Image: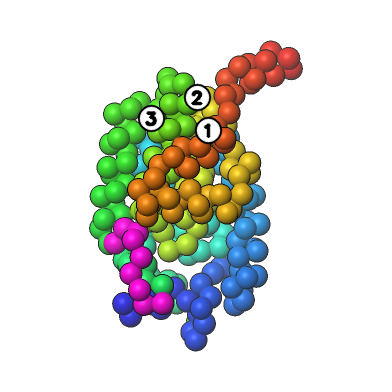
Amino acid sequence: HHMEHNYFYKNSATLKNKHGIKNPRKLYERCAHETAREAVNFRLEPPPGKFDAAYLRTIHWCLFHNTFEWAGVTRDQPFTFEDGSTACMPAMRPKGYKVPFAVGSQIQRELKKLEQRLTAKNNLQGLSRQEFAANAAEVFTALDHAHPFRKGNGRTQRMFMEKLGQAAGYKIDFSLITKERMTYASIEAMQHNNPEPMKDLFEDITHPQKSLLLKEFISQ
Ligand SMILES: [Br-]
Ligand SMILES: [Cl-]
């Protein structure tokens, strides 16, 4: 427990970061700006053969390394800052209460089980738009629950979905959807055992690209 605090500046609830910012809202704004810039290039990268914990670490590093020393490192892992201090957070405990996200080494076991399900399904390549959306919703819910990093989980997870989609010929567009909707769908699937909303959300954000790109390509 005592190591949790070493993610933050002394006497503050602000995450240590490479910009030196000590206001948590301003940190958020700068972090949003830096990761948006990095996501533009990461979208053009070729996809790996496995969608696993190493790939998630790769995404997290690529998106957050300008902001966080521990970019690419999961929160179950002791991390030592340049300042000498060592941080980790095996359990999310807001206000001292347990919330139902993966704890400790459960993070790695959940990500493993997710790679194994995806690998066995050829990473969802060769499926209809609807069937892809229905599986992709389940993947998204698995990642919600894993919450592998200290911070940056949402953007990391969305990017993982974009790349899985892209490798299957689909644009996954989270800009189509409101925050309130994503929260509703996440809680339904995680707390109320109700997959339908996340399924309907993925049907709304999964758009076939193969044919459009081929048209564009030939016109050019
Ligand atoms: Br982003
Ligand atoms: Cl400090």
Q: Is residue 101 magenta?
A: yes
190 or 72: which is nearer to us?
190
* Disc 1 crowd, CA 10 A, few/some/many (<14, 14-19, 20+): some
Picture residue at 57% right of the left edge, 59% below the top: 66
Q: Given this view, does label 1 or label 3 mark the residue nearer the observer?
A: 1
Name the N-terminal-most of marks 1 and 3: 3
Where disc 1 sits, the SS reads: helix
Q: Is mark 2 within 8 Å of ligand 1?
A: no
User: Which quarter of the rendered picture does the N terminus lie within?
Assistant: bottom left
* Residue under pointer 2: 129
Q: CA distance from mark 3 to mark 2?
A: 14 Å
- The structure's colour scheme is rainbow
Which three-letter amino acid code belongs to the residue tagged 1? Answer: Glu
Residue 211 vertical position relative to residue 116 in the rendered view, above or below: above
Magenta residues span: 95-103
Query: Which residue is denoted by mark 3 in the rendering?
Result: 123
Q: Residue at x 25, y 58 (%)?
A: 105
- SS category of the residue bearing label 3: helix
Q: Is residue 50 left or right of residue 214?
A: left
The answer to whether residue 216 is visible is yes
Judged left or right of residue 218, residue 152 is: left
Q: Which residue is mark 1?
A: 203
